[PDB]
Amino acid sequence: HYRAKLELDRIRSMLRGRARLERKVGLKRLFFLMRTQTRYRVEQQAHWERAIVRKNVDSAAREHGTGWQHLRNELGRQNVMLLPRSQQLLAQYEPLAFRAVVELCASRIPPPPPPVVASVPEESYTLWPPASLSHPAARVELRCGVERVLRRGPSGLGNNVNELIDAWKEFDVSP
Amino acid sequence: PEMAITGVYRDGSERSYNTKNLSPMGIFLRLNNLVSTANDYDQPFCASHLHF
Amino acid sequence: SSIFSPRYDWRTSGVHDIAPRDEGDFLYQGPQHVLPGAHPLPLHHPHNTITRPVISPYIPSPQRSHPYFTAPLPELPHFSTTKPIVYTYGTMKERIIAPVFNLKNEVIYTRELDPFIFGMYPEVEELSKNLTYWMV
Amino acid sequence: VYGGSGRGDLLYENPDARRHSGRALGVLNGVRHSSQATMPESGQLYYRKLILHSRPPNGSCAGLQRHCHDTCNWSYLIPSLHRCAESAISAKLWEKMCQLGLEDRSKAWVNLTQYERQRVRDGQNLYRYEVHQRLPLLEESIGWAQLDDLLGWFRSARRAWVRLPTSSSAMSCRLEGHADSRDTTPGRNQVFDTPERVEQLTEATVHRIREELQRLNRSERSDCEGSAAMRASARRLARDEELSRCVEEELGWHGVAL
Amino acid sequence: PKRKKNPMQLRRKVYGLHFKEKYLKMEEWYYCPLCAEPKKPGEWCRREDCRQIKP
Amino acid sequence: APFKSVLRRHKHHPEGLPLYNDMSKQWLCREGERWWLLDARGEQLPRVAAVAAQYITGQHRPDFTPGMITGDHVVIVNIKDVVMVGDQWIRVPITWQTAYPGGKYRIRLTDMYERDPCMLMWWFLKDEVNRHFVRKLKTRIAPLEKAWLYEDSIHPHADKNPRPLCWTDPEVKGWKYRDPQFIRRWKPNEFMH
RNA sequence: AUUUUACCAAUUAAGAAGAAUAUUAUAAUAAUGGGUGUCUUAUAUUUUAAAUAAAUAUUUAAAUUCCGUGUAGUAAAUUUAUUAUUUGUAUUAUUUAUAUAAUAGGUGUAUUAUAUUUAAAUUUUAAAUUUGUUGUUUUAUAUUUAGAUACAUAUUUAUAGAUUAAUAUAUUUAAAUAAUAUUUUAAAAUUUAUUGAAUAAAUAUAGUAAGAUUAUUUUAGUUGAAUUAAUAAAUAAAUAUUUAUUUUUCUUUGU
Ligand SMILES: [Mg+2]
Ligand SMILES: [Mg+2]
Ligand SMILES: [Mg+2]
Ligand SMILES: [Mg+2]
Ligand SMILES: [Mg+2]
Ligand SMILES: [Mg+2]
Ligand SMILES: [Zn+2]
């Protein structure tokens, strides 16, 4: 049996009275305290914390005219994906933003469509070679890739796509 | 020699690690932990402590 | 304490004095600085040549099988082994000649050893058996 | 810094190291969280503050309801240095050194034994250490010092055989050590220019001795003018003469001239 | 059923008035005008002066 | 270690019990305190008690913290005209226990109403509060003092200007009804094509 | 006109020859009962007998026999011998005290849920016995200190069948020759003596009642089965330690 004695000896100053004066009583008290605190943190703390945050968000929504039920359902529908912690943070520190979220949920704005399944380009069915050129599907994939490259932030590569695709022609030395 | 490494920071704080019969790889790891931490505070990791 | 133990690193300050000594403490200059005792291999006994002098023709090197001679020196009398040389299962399979010394710290001549006696390559199991029997 | 060693304490205790204990540290007095056991995070300011302020008052801490000794007084700091010099160098060795110096001008040291040489060196070292310790309190008390102790400031140095610097001599150089490794943490009163601060302190105390002598002379002259008669006490006359001769000789020994 | 009592139960007695008025309480005294001694009002000295007149 | 002194206040003690409206504790805020008016004409007792408690305990605030006991002052008016559905004023029991043996007092809602109409509202507020705060005497007593009950319509709280709090009961619901039949309006283009 | 609320806190350096011809084995050479503050004589100062005892023994066969309680000279006077205070503190190891104490005048609270300081949220302590696994039984004031014994291993000299009841028969492959020990406290009065129910021996033994049995952070199988006294019938099952079978298949499977 490994009784946590040498570790819990240093926390006896937090206790009072006989538990702090004597050793074994304080060690038993600290052992029981740590065990019950671990049990509560594992199996019962999250329930109370999430209930508190849910009640705060529900009160913030009721001050605007809705409830936690409808707000949560419409957030899931509109696919906003905001955790209750973030909802509470917005309700407490960004009331205008939270009110705008509520107005979005209340309005008849079309929610985004489901993600489109990855399709195959029409050129993949073309005979190649038809009889030193690139595959048409591969060229279209490269064009879409360069488009996505230029779409993310501003960079010195330029907005045009043909000149950036034809970089191997530039790197090629004229024989 | 005291089998321990000490880190003295730019605010007088001192952080010591025990390296008795500890491999040099572990010694290097503890030294990098020393140079990585600032040793200016100690706060838990919770939803209320995410933002300082 | 144990390495994987919570009691191992609860002494987080005070073990060292912030102020260093003025006679023996020094700063690390850089990679070209030769630290006293620094060695990549773990040497619990860091004894070197000067502190623990070795007496042999050559310093034991990975190129040389044994630090002693391999062929009789033409300027020193060579004495063959009293009994003929046989190479057994554990012998070094190489000729070993030791430079016999005199009481005046001068090499007198060179005498060949026996690989069965001084060529049986050591083994930790047998060394540990001997040591354990002696200490018990 | 509160419990271990104060500002003018000659003691040296590492506040985080329990080197004055006959038992392993079982209970930690200053504890804020249950996680302070397996990793007390000591050395951080916000926790070592709690620990060192929960520590009890020691003999030098002078707890609140208990009386606190007068330490910042020049009239106490000077006899401290004098008693340290007497504890370092005995009277017989002091007389032998004085005779040897007045006879050979620091040239016949061969008569002294190696043990006596080492005693003199250790005494000079301890005097330098205690001067480095008392330097802040001395610079604090230089304002309201008295002439007797201002002269004892040089008397103690002469007795300890330490020539004070002026812009043997042991206060001329600093302790060797690279500035990148020397201790510089705040909260610990440690001067870094000892030959530069003690020299200006000697200049200031010379000016203060001159001011005190002039104040005594002016007070005597004003008293004589108020009495409208030249009737001086024999005690006061003898005291003035002997103090003038003493300050002259003891400042000439160190090398300072008014 | 009797058991050891914690230090808190040992300090409950000083909260009552019975403990305060018994042990820790000061006196109302003055100086005997005839003996120059501390004297409580009501109790006198053996001397002839203190018996005839009450100091 | 925290320590609560045994020498606490008592009802027989001459110092008496305090008013949380007058206290100045740390966990008691008074800046964000609004005054609401709640008319109880027709509204049922448990519903009006829940609506009042949700504003008393400060649960309607987004920054509500269980420790900090902050809330709004609700002034309930026309408690004498409160309405409960039939047979409840006679059947609903209110019981309690006293220190004497066999002292199990059991009174009807009618009896408590003819004694004092405010007692019913106070009892239901106590129940709605103890539903969530029963552990700490502070958290279960301090909210109740923020309710200002008044039997008749008159009240001295005219300076605070109580706002007429509006609240909707969770009972309102429209059961499906028959689709009404009406004549259809046609269109010339529809008749053409 | 006097005039500082109640409650709430802490073990640490140790001053001193107040630590040694010190404890326990170890000496193979002496020995007529030791009694100093002692001290006349002894019809009054006598203990002896062919056995297992202050003398103590290098093996596993066979064999009497209704649990085989078992091994013989290695040398014939040969060097396994009952040793002891100093010509090494005898040497070599091992162990060792229970006298002496200034420490803080207030961090959480003040109408009552029990340490982590933003106030809430959490609980009644452990170890054994109860197999109908409890609400049954028993123990624990605290501090310090004693307290319990199956060898996790095998390097060249080197060489290892069986089988009939027996006389016999022998055409089949290996091997790291090493033994010594095996919880603790107790559950009972008979024994062997002595002195007028006590005294001193017996780890004697109880098919054996009951309890205690010192060492965290770990890395792989079954959670109610099995149950045939006794001529030629494939096989008891669980638990645990080591250890072995890579065959097909649409995925899976602790045999
Ligand atoms: Mg969790
Ligand atoms: Mg307090
Ligand atoms: Mg002692
Ligand atoms: Mg003999
Ligand atoms: Mg023990
Ligand atoms: Mg198995
Ligand atoms: Zn009198």
Image (cartoon, helix red, strand yellow):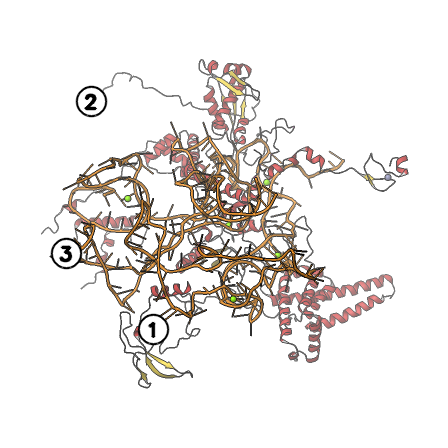
Circles 1 and 3 on the same chain:
no
Q: Secondary structure at mark 2?
A: helix
- Closest to the observer: D104 or C7? C7
Q: Secondary structure at mark 3?
A: loop
Q: Is residue D117 left or right of residue F94?
A: right
Magenta-drawn segment: F1-19
Compared to residue A122, the image places residue F172 above or below, namely: above
Tell me the amino acid under the disc marked 1: Ser
Report which residue position mark 2 lands on: F190
Residue D171's x, y, as percent?
62, 69
Residue B9 visible in the shown view: no
Residue A153's x, y, as percent?
32, 49
Residue D145 visible in the shown view: yes
Report which residue position mark 1 lands on: C61
Asked if the stretch drawn in magenta spans residue F3, the answer is yes
**Cβ–Cβ under 8 Å for marks 1 and 3:** no
Residue G159's x, y, as percent?
24, 63
Report which residue position mark 3 lands on: A132
| Residue reaching furthest to the bottom | C75
Task: Say which residue appears at 29% left-offset and 17% top-offset.
Answer: F178
Circles 1 and 2 on the same chain:
no
